[PDB]
Image 1 (cartoon, rainbow, N blue to C red):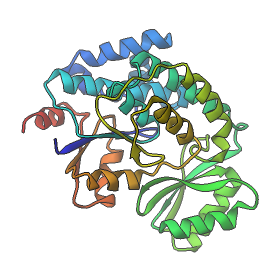
Image 2 (image 1 turned 90 degrees about the vertical axis):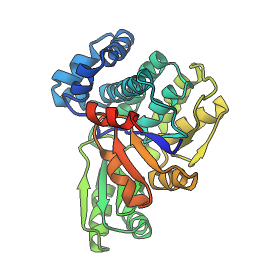
Image 3 (image 1 turned 45 degrees about the vertical axis):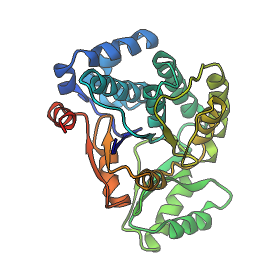
Image 4 (image 1 turned 90 degrees about the horizontal axis):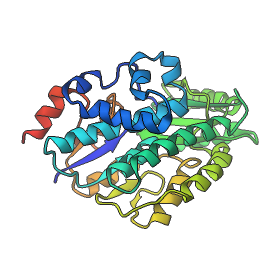
Length: 308
């Protein structure tokens, strides 16, 4: 086919997410019921009632996001939707893609990402880390501002979301210094994210070590749909290969801009965002303007996408 499926991560959750899709297809709440049975609490109720402060806790956000994406995948299949040529995910999103591609058992994945969130949250002492979105400054300048600002601490470009949108992370003070340096180098803005965990940088090392232990116990099967990982920007099929990329993903940058450039290089013409929100959808044209993108979280939109 001429489309790929892309899966979003932290930031795309919202209270009330998938409410209309759930009204359209009972399989949405059934999928969440399966996750809820593995988690020991009503995941659907949490996404619908919140409060946002709870849904935003990473060990709850991750299963909520994975489940939401798997639910849309199941709706797509139920209605006869064809298989994408390739899949890709943004951090947590990679797990969604791996579940949809048949590599990891859904309940296993739900338990896995819950732990992933817990490990990440404990990596560093409360309030010592930070992430900031740098807007309107080239990758070279951002890297230079980070090097100048590190002063022995950690601060690196960690999410390459698009040209003009790079999230940096590390020790909070280093991130505050790097943001200011980025602005002085021409950045339009430096916007701290609402997360307290410095994802995708060296400080996640301990979390990655614990995750690798838990991942080693989960049976990885052969993918029935190809998945390009965001840490190396390539497709792996060997379980050990997929695992190690997941381990390394946690403390290495998400090369989203390169992953989308790679998808376009394969000849894919359209990206469908399989999850809540329209985050990935928005980045697409900024990365490769020959692509089109749309989200699959609204009933009318999913209905239209099937018809072609």
